[PDB]
Amino acid sequence: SRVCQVTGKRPVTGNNRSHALNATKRRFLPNLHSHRFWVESEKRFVTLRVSAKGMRVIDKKGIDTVLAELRARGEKY
Amino acid sequence: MQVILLDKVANLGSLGDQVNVKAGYARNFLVPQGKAVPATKKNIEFFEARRAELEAKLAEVLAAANARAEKINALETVTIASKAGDEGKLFGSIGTRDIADAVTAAGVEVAKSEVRLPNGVLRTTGEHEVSFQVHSEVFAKVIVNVVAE
RNA sequence: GCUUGACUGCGAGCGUGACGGCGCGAGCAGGUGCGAAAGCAGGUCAUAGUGAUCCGGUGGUUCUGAAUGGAAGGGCCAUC
RNA sequence: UGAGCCUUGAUGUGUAGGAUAGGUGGGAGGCUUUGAAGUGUGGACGCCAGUCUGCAUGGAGCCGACCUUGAAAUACCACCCUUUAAUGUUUGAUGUUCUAACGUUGACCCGUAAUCCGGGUUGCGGACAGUGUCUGGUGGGUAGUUUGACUGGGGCGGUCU
RNA sequence: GUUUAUUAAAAACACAGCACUGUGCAAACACGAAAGUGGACGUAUACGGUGUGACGCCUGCCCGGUGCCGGAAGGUUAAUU
RNA sequence: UUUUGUAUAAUGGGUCAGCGACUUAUAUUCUGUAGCAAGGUUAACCGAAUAGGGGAGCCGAAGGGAAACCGAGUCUUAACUGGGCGUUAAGUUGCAGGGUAUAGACCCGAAACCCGGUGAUCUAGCCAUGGGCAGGUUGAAGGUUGGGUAACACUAACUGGAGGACCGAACCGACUAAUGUUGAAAAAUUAGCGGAUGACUUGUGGCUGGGGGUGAAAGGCCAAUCAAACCGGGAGAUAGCU
RNA sequence: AGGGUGACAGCCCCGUACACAAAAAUGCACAUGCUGUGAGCUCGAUGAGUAGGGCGGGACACGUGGUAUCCUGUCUGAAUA
RNA sequence: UAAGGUGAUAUGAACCGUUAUAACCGGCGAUUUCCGAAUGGGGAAACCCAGUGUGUUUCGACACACUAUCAUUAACUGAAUCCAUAGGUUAAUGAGGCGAACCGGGGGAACUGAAACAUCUAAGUACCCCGAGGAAAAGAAAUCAACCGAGAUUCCCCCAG
Ligand SMILES: [Mg+2]
Ligand SMILES: [Mg+2]
Ligand SMILES: [Mg+2]
Ligand SMILES: [Mg+2]
Ligand SMILES: [Mg+2]
Ligand SMILES: [Mg+2]
Ligand SMILES: [Mg+2]
Ligand SMILES: [Mg+2]
Ligand SMILES: [Mg+2]
Ligand SMILES: [Mg+2]
Ligand SMILES: [Mg+2]
Ligand SMILES: [Mg+2]
Ligand SMILES: [Mg+2]
Ligand SMILES: [Mg+2]
Ligand SMILES: [Mg+2]
Ligand SMILES: [Mg+2]
Ligand SMILES: [Mg+2]
Ligand SMILES: [Mg+2]
Ligand SMILES: [Mg+2]
Ligand SMILES: [Mg+2]
Ligand SMILES: [Mg+2]
Ligand SMILES: [Mg+2]
Ligand SMILES: [Mg+2]
Ligand SMILES: [Mg+2]
Ligand SMILES: [Mg+2]
Ligand SMILES: [Mg+2]
Ligand SMILES: [Mg+2]
Ligand SMILES: [Mg+2]
Ligand SMILES: [Mg+2]
Ligand SMILES: [Mg+2]
Ligand SMILES: [Mg+2]
Ligand SMILES: [Mg+2]
Ligand SMILES: [Mg+2]
Ligand SMILES: [Mg+2]
Ligand SMILES: [Mg+2]
Ligand SMILES: [Mg+2]
Ligand SMILES: [Mg+2]
Ligand SMILES: [Mg+2]
Ligand SMILES: [Mg+2]
């Protein structure tokens, strides 16, 4: 599914509002990308389905910190 | 993205320098190949503590080397007995081991490596000047007494 | 010829409307023009020439102003 | 390569004149064998007067109150201007290349007696493509609707204050 | 040949043939928010869409309008700043 | 019943029996009635439980003005000779009733719109695997031989067995007529009719699903009424109509 | 209270008021045993891709309005009693 | 607890019992085919077919037990590729499915009302989906108030149409 493995960001629903204020149901999808992260501690690359926001979270916290959250959640990588 | 460099990287800086880099350069090249680390408040302290620890350890070594450099000039004349023939020509020579072991027994604990001779290895009876490398910049002189045995 | 009554606030009493409204009005107060004066003038001989409300704009204002002083916004008056 | 900055080099016909006087200051020796004068010539500027400068040659000098001139020595040095060139830096623009993100519906290895998938190797691409959010255009493909009343039936015509 | 099973079998639809047009393959196109699949285990003598309708003799003029294709100089023009 | 007007040849009712349509809740106002009265009444809750407690509130005894504010007055205007609204009419809480408001709001009735399911046992197209086509004709290409030609062409006889070929049963279809039309049959029967080796026909099983399918295209077909199936739900949709 | 009994029952029958009852299993309370968990005191520490912001939506009685507050799909991004 | 009993249509038959293993009532046990989550594999539910381990005064074939998937944990094992990691086997423990309403969350109509209709309404309703408990959710102030103060959440009556 279109779910960020880091933040949990998923498709949300809302409306397209026209100039005439006609509401039509829509979705806002997360900016998802499958990215290979180098994990020094495991001497292996880990491919995660992450939003650009989640990628910034990994830049701040570090991949080991983020992967530890995935283990605690039971979420495999 | 602020990062503190581990190695020497072109156009950026040197080891321990704090530079602003594009997130993708750090993420996909600099951090995986160990050329840099994120400039986090924990690591900025760890690298400033190492900068202060190296500055204090380099100032004390500059203080110990100058105490050694003033002890080398204090002796001013060291006597070395060597078997020399007629006209003053030595059968052997007075090398680095010979000069270094003469000053260690005199007081100043100088190494074989620290001794620096210009052209010869001392093959004549008389007086000669011997310069010393105590540190990369600190230099001090002594006069060697070539006494015939 | 001289001029700004094409005045501002009101209005006894009426007309005509299911209503929203629309009309006629002497007289009162303030200030004004014309006339020597009595007087006349609140547009045009009269009856067509028009668009409610909402929303919004502009100016004015002893009104209001979400702790309090302001301000925003709202009201009231004029107008688009 | 447009624009800001930085060391450092070019460039200046009031007249008395050794002569195309840069303002203001340190102000008695600098510039030299890390090799001047003087000659030969190349290049650039230009007010065809001459300045700056490359190379060769040559070899013991061009110089100061020395008198003019408001203001000084091309003996030398420091902030700069009239303007111009070029090395360093900043954010742009444009191009070339790179590999490491990312693509592979090329080949191979393993999981594995598997035309899926994953990991790995390798080749080809490559910051492009593609995707997310935002945005202009298009969009009967789909969707929801509107499309008036009077009227000798209705429609046409006409009408509506 | 096909068709309105149950009032229409026809001159209607289809047809071989013709033409225009798209499509270089992870094709265009189509079913799918996607993954996957059909096209096709095909590859421009192929595949899709559109029109015309064996064959014979043939198919003239018009690009103003509407649709499409190509163009980049100028004018106007979104988010953004 | 509906109408200007119905014996009306306008509507409705075969007859009987039973059932079948102005309700209910909460607001709100008015009338009647009762209590108390410049006051009236409590709500939730507590409870000793239809008592009693609880006055939080609500309505009323004050209005005028957009308001600040002033107040039996106030607003209007600089101010009214004035003018507008007010002051001189008792209210409030039950209970019953008349109206109204929100609700299905007197009962019954659409054609439809939306949502979630069930359906390709009928039929459309396709996929896999099987089966069927009596009898009679026509006689393509090719081949052999003879004639022919310089050689070919060409030509005759034979052989050969093509085709969405011909005639015609089964099988598939459905052009005409009569019958039938409360049928033997919710599409047939009888006499004739077209195709009948093909783009043929048929069995068994599979796949496509409702703004969807499938369609040699008729808006055809998708389980006996398809310009949007069927079932259940939103649901008592709405119905200025009968 | 009520029901039944050949018609309508306080006194016929079953009940009703009232008074009682569990070998066994179980609910809830306290008392208490055990395993695990930790009380009190002193000195610290004080939740960052967060708050805030731009864009698109949604939620607030409040429909973008002069619109505070909340959530966040996208791009960003603090201070530290 | 008992003088009567072997449930009903529903007799009859053969019987059981009367002072306490007749029956009847309640607590705890035993047994509980096959299908169904269905779980050894399959399947058109109540059927078809196995592997392994065990039993056979008959050790053929039948009977009996175990063998699904996933999650966590452990042991053994074990690639590409040296370590590692993936993968593989086994064991322990848990889950699964069903079912009223209420409850938290993910999605989310339209008819209708506006006397048409699009903003708005219907309505976060109907419905679909996930999850949970005896309740759920919420909850101990980056809350209000107004210069006086209150002191988490939930629910009721007012404020007030
Ligand atoms: Mg006068
Ligand atoms: Mg204030
Ligand atoms: Mg792009
Ligand atoms: Mg847009
Ligand atoms: Mg359009
Ligand atoms: Mg349409
Ligand atoms: Mg509608
Ligand atoms: Mg009409
Ligand atoms: Mg035919
Ligand atoms: Mg027909
Ligand atoms: Mg017919
Ligand atoms: Mg045609
Ligand atoms: Mg033509
Ligand atoms: Mg064009
Ligand atoms: Mg009539
Ligand atoms: Mg009559
Ligand atoms: Mg009649
Ligand atoms: Mg009748
Ligand atoms: Mg009253
Ligand atoms: Mg035939
Ligand atoms: Mg027949
Ligand atoms: Mg015939
Ligand atoms: Mg025939
Ligand atoms: Mg079939
Ligand atoms: Mg409804
Ligand atoms: Mg109805
Ligand atoms: Mg009797
Ligand atoms: Mg805190
Ligand atoms: Mg906040
Ligand atoms: Mg406004
Ligand atoms: Mg099974
Ligand atoms: Mg089984
Ligand atoms: Mg089997
Ligand atoms: Mg290995
Ligand atoms: Mg369950
Ligand atoms: Mg409507
Ligand atoms: Mg439970
Ligand atoms: Mg709870
Ligand atoms: Mg306080």
Image (cartoon, coloured by chain):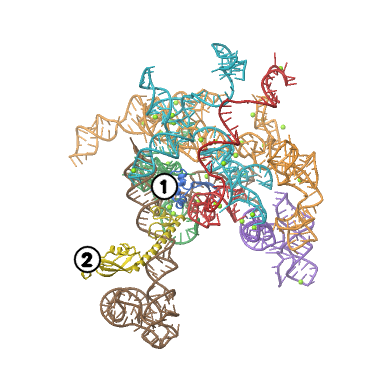
Chain colours: A blue, B yellow, C purple, D brown, E green, F orange, G red, H cyan
Q: Nearer the viewer, residue F199 or D110?
A: D110
Is C34 situated above or below E22?
Answer: below
Mark drawn on residue B91? 2
Q: Nearer the viewer, residue H156 or C38?
A: H156
Q: Which quadrant does ligand 37 occupy? A: top right
Of the residues tagged 1 and 2, which is closer to the observer?
2
| Mark 2: few/some/many CA within 10 Å (<14, 14-19, 20+) | few
Residue at 25%, 69% in the rendered image: B125
In the rendered image, the quadrant that contains the C terminus of chain B is bottom left
In the rendered image, the quadrant that contains the N terminus of chain B is bottom left
Q: Establish whether labels 1 and 2 are both on one chain.
A: no
Q: Position of residue F204 (x, y in %)?
A: 42, 28
Please tell me whether mark 2 sits on a helix, a strand or a loop. loop
Is F241 situated above or below B59?
Answer: above
Q: Amino acid at mark 1?
A: Thr
Query: Where is mark 1, residue-wise?
Result: A47
Q: Nearer the viewer, residue F57 or E81?
A: F57
Q: Amino acid at mark 2?
A: Phe
Q: Position of residue E34 (x, y in %)?
A: 44, 44
Q: Position of residue C68 (x, y in %)?
A: 66, 58
Total labels: the figure holds: 2
Report in which chain the residue with disc 2 lies. B
**In-image side of E16 versus A18 (left or right):** left
Residue at 38%, 48% in the rendered image: A43
Whether residue A32 is visible, yes or no, is no
Residue at 40%, 62% in the rendered image: B60
